[PDB]
Image (tube, each protein chain N blue to C red):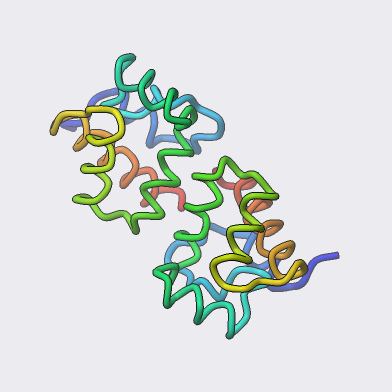
Length: 89
Length: 88
């Protein structure tokens, strides 16, 4: 296992109303910027991931443009949503 | 009241189900959604989620996007809402 514990905790169960900061790669700084843009719950970011048809390039670019995420942060967030979807969607 | 199509959709994860598996989305609406990029049910779920599950805005978006009437958009909203309550 090379993922974080935080990734593993997110992908282990339905997300319900978890805040956006429950996503791997989304620390307090990125989480506040996402909340200020209306992406306050993790499921709203899931929504964007799905509207983009789970495309890595589009989602990771969107995250960068929306909250300033760097490459590692955006990879971690994408991977957490991708594995959650494989488990639950 | 619900259709069997609704109950079949809300009973299980949607995976890669086509957009036409959603209650309310018949052959005509489905084609118009596919033409606009919403080829899978989960892409419409995505829009429902981006809109924070807001009934008025989602049903209006669906009217604007594929011409859904009030019953079709009612049916589609209700199946996504109940799916999310079971699985999200």
